Length: 428
Ligand SMILES: [Ca+2]
Ligand SMILES: [Cl-]
Ligand SMILES: [Fe+3]
Ligand SMILES: [Mg+2]
Image (cartoon, rainbow, N blue to C red):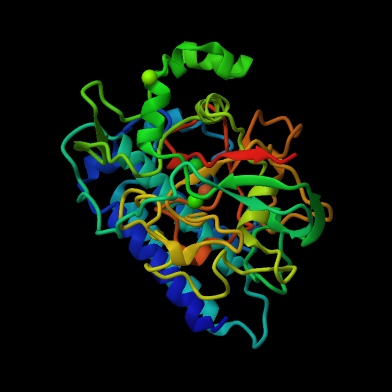
């Protein structure tokens, strides 16, 4: 954009990062849960990736500030999450110094870029840092003990008449994905724009709520194998799943260390893919495919056009969606009527990541971005395991990095992520 706007975005991302590591060194070195890196790992990894993609042209053979063996401590493919707490990592002071040195050089580089030069990598790195900010939030939510963060900023109230209900998405061709011409910082797996024929289906007007999930629990949903897939039931049994994560026996939940009543009308959060598909079956529905999801989000059947956001082309605001990290929770269903898609689906962007039944697959014409290992290793059959795509962003996602076409994914056994469920149905 303006180089000034990119600088602004990089600086906002780093402000966020530095708030999330504004704790004692011992906190930053802790393993809150074996699923998660220590925060000091994400801190240095953020700087190392910024250096690699913006100062070293993505070529690790070009010299960096760190010895290559030190740099490789921050290679996510080499070091499984659980092992990272024991690695000989840079201290918090070293990591902050490294990040600052890199950032100074990056801002100078941005200044010096020729007019009309390609800036894709800068936007890619903004996305990378904000994504790690959400990862660090996941870790802080898992942390046992008295809260470090506050309990979250105010959200609007919900409204009656939306929970449980569905909207029709009329059948036919629509444009899936985007081109760089339209979204200059769309990540590689979002591209290119192409047509897919999607038969008529219905999708939930809002996500599944906590009170709805409690009904599933109360009817014995976790005790009845018929709602679950073979793999899902086996995992439910292995892991002893009986409720969403952080729901306590006494009916409270623990959210960033805060013990509180579970609000009935918020989207359910911290459920596995396997839980999501079991609830959907028990409810008489199914999960959407990600293609269904994106059509419901972005397509306007009255005009036969894609919208930039579900509501139109206006930049996200606090009146339109719950984004950016400050709320530390999703909003009550019905809280954002102005954020509805053309078909009437609300809270598609923000609040909770929504499970879909789609594995990650390339769109026809896919070509990798400079960070070649960002998507490709996770495509179905690429040999990295089983993944399902999540859509729409959560309350923790920065508005700057989110689009209807954005594709998250994870193993179906993961629920420390800020994920919930929106139902779908076939139409006859
Ligand atoms: Ca969402
Ligand atoms: Cl990671
Ligand atoms: Fe990363
Ligand atoms: Mg009953």
